[PDB]
Image: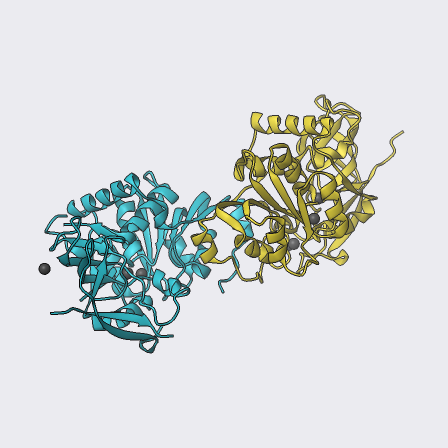
Chain colours: A cyan, B yellow
Amino acid sequence: FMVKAKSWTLKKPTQSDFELKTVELPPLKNGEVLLEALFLSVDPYMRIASKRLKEGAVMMGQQVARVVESKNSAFPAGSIVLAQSGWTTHFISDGKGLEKLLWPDKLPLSLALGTIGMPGLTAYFGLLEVCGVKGGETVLVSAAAGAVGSVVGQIAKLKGCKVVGAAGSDEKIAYLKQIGFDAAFNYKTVNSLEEALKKASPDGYDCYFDNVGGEFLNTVLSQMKDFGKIAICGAISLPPGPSPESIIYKQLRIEGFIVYRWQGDVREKALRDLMKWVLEGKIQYHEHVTKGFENMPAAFIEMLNGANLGKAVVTA
Amino acid sequence: PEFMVKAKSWTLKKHFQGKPTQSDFELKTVELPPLKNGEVLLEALFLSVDPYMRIASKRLKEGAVMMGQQVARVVESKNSAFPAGSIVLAQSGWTTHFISDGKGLEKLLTEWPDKLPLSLALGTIGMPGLTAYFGLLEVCGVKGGETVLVSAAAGAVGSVVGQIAKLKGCKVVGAAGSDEKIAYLKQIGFDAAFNYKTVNSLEEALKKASPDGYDCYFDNVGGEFLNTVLSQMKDFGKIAICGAISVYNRMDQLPPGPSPESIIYKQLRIEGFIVYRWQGDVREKALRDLMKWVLEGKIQYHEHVTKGFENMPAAFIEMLNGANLGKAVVTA
Ligand SMILES: [Cl-]
Ligand SMILES: [Cl-]
Ligand SMILES: [Cl-]
Ligand SMILES: [Cl-]
Ligand SMILES: [Cl-]
Ligand SMILES: [Cl-]
Ligand SMILES: [Cl-]
């Protein structure tokens, strides 16, 4: 009985720019493993990475998958792994891009795609290393209700900082207050972004974890404390020019970073911290689940437009 | 026999709207009162015009004297701390003469070497030279071997940056505003230099000057140029934001900003700084280093001297255009 792998290829975002292809996978050769997707991730970074993706190719992505059949002793049948296999239901691998797992049974495996995964790590190094928080600071976080934002705010809180979050809906604002943000506002409905930031924090901000860029970032600059630090993580919002006056006179430090910069022991340690914090209830998690591999492009679309509260996860 | 002194001062007649013009200034002449005990009468010898004045002027009240530092001689004194004849650096603004009770008088230039023009105290061995020293050595944080790019390379700051970089064993590329400036930069030691105002492609000029890209960008210009430089930075590259001359005349209508994608993927570090950050012994050490370097010939200098106090506004306008080669200095 042969297995049929369904994959989402980039046709030309909108549904029409995605095309599902089906292929019968060949038998396993020695050293290979047959994997079945359990939970697939859709992330903001994909919209950009789609660039060098020649049409017809399977979309890039990470997923949590189970080993169904195996001829690889490192990955026995029944094993659960993290793979960079892209948007596909089944795939064959010689073990190249796979990471081990089964991890407390009480934690859903899909957390390895979010809070105890890439987004969680982005939040961790972004806040603890780029911003360099040590406690007592006032931290601003944009797209605060997203996968990265939600973690940044909760880590800031456990480190004893005052935390302000900017999100895209009133539903999200209630959520942020629920996970511990000291202040939270809908940046889309502000009368004055400048005054909202002032209201949120009269004395300004020590660190700004940026996921939006553009106008938001520019306005934030004027409210940074001297020697303030801005960690450029993403830019969901051509952006208007920043004021040189603020950067120079307040002597601000702006640094862009990619989570992949940190590897080895430091990365392993950060994942243990993230898992520990989740087990201690210090970092609550929420996954916006879309059921059905057939609904992945839609899930991807829904996420990009901000209809997602927390980590976007698609179940096979 | 008391003869009165008349002080001439350049006042900001109207706040700058876009590029400053002669009509924005108004010369005033005033009869100075006699000195009271504890006061001193100073006569400007050399006056400075600097990029920061374009922005600092926004805080002035119309009719006020333009701000600025100058080297002045104490003509008469009733203040024991400033004897008649002494030379001082003072923040008295654009004025030929002024009375001070000690306020504004930053320091005596008593130990100054005669072979060095006093105006170097306003440039290479002054604020611009300090800005370059700390911007390069502390912000860019060079250790040697890096490839440094500096905009407005032939200006007061840029000229010093490139020279200190060279003594530190760095490769230096200068983006200057004229062909004469290119020749000058090469003569003082820059490894490469191009005219960013005439080169067909800024991208190709940067690539040609350094195929492997840049470790630090000492930014004096900002704007479109800065945005273009980001694509040429090496991963983890550092950009020291010193000034933004290309946008000082359009702070209310700024051009598009830098690519978030370049900053993120190249993982760049941008830091603004002002020379005020370094005070005390650290600043004194820098000044001593700057003077030693100038006396030894390791740091060459050129002053862009405009003769006559009545030409100060034009000197300021020219410098703002980035057209001065070396420190813009006005002789009274
Ligand atoms: Cl199985
Ligand atoms: Cl959000
Ligand atoms: Cl997400
Ligand atoms: Cl003005
Ligand atoms: Cl006014
Ligand atoms: Cl120049
Ligand atoms: Cl100058």
Identify whether A13 is placed above or below B323. Answer: below
Q: Is residue B9 left or right of residue B207?
A: right
Q: Is residue A102 left or right of residue A168?
A: left
- Please provide percent x and percent y for residue B141: 53, 36
- Please provide percent x and percent y for residue B35: 77, 30
User: Outermost residue, right direction?
Assistant: B1
Q: Can the viewer see residue B130 in this picture?
A: no
User: Outermost residue, front direction?
Assistant: A30
- Please provide percent x and percent y for residue B67: 68, 44
Write down the quadrant of residue A168 in the picture: bottom left
Q: Residue at x 72, y 55 (%)?
A: B13
* The C terminus of chain B lies in quadrant: top right
Identify whether B9 is placed above or below B23. Answer: above
Write down the quadrant of residue B299 in the picture: top right
Depth check: give the residue in front, A83 or B132: A83
Depth check: give the residue in front, B283 or B302: B302
Write down the quadrant of residue A20 in the picture: bottom left
Q: Residue at x 70, y 47 (%)?
A: B66
Depth check: give the residue in front, A111 or A190: A111
- Please provide percent x and percent y for residue A138: 35, 45
Identify whether B298 is placed above or below A274. Answer: above
Q: Please tell me in which quarter of the rendered image ligand 7 is found.
A: top right
Q: Residue at x 26, y 66 (%)?
A: A87
